[PDB]
Image (tube, rainbow over all chains, first blue to last red; front, side, top):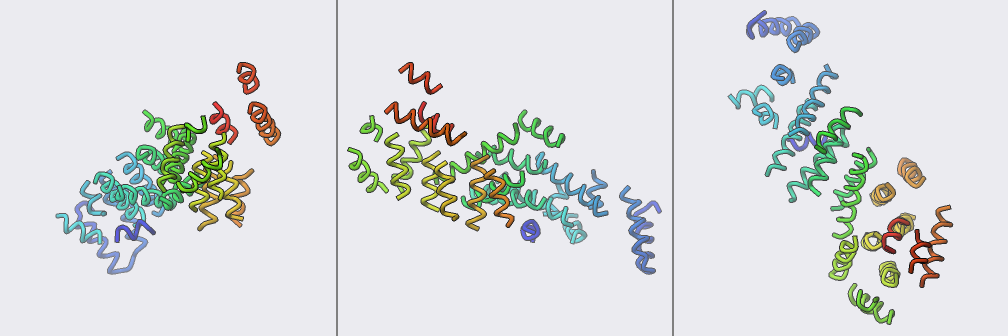
Length: 8
Length: 177
Length: 98
Length: 36
């Protein structure tokens, strides 16, 4: 979740 | 209002009557380092983001929560926040070869999304000194004031040239591989 | 190599046999450095992988080879060219934007 | 002009194939480095 929000 | 309860009462009345513009104003009054952390309108959020990025480049409980404690996690449950969380994860990875590469990639991605940040990234790359990495370096070169220069000077304790040199070195390394 | 330099076709055949270990050795020699031999090498390399080897050795030849091959891949090439050069840059940028 | 300079360099290299030579000498940068 935290790494999906960083990629966005 | 003085207590927390007082404020919550106010808010409860703004809810009960649907006064979002009022609540927004009250809160605005409340917002006016720990206080800033508690607060985390668009411009302000952006500024907070920038500050967080600067702190990360320079580099506790709040940071962990972003990435008594359970209650805080529940309360937390935005873009600025996500970015700070990513920066924290990157630093953690750094503290912990492939991991380092993943962190560097994350950093390049963040830079692309966003001058000072770019400089910090370049500094990190120089300190570290395949195809994906090269592509990232290239994008950075393509992307490439006083505060930035000062930061560069602090780090050294010309910048563009050093960056170009580092890029050349990376390219050479990729060619050797 | 350095010994004989200080029978050219013979060396061409030897390097022909050489062509990964050979590439690594060449990279090592280039790193250490940082005529006839150079020309022979360039010719053998000219005989992704190809472009890379060519570039590594020449370190203009690189740029020429890349441009010829180009005449994701596009972006990577343009980028590599711009970094190496740092008129050409402007043209590359315009092409990538078009 | 750069092309002409490169041509002159190539011609000099062909002619070479000591002090006078050094006097005459005094990507292009890479070539010069390889020469030295």
